[PDB]
Length: 87
Length: 44
Image (cartoon, rainbow over all chains, first blue to last red; front, side, top):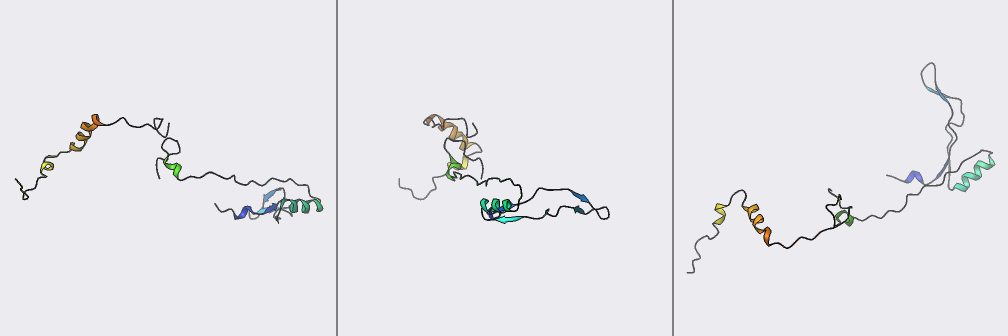
């Protein structure tokens, strides 16, 4: 339930091939950017960084949870379906 | 006739398994009609 890892913007790159090492079965890669993850304060900072580096990019809008209407008293409604059958 | 020396709650010596529910069944005719929530249950 913690939300502290949803505060900042991230930039990552498209995933590329990983294959099994013939000797040990380890995951090999030829992609030098496979682990690069950048952190940004705002979407505009992330876009600015990508542009000046010449990277094509996609932006995904932030998904804030919408405010909910919570009422403990609703658990015990006289004539509504929100009445709980158990606690 | 003021006898303050005997126990006058002896009726319950003759109560049985269904005494309470028989009285509730007997009382059924004296009740007012119940209120309604508007539906058969919270799951309706």
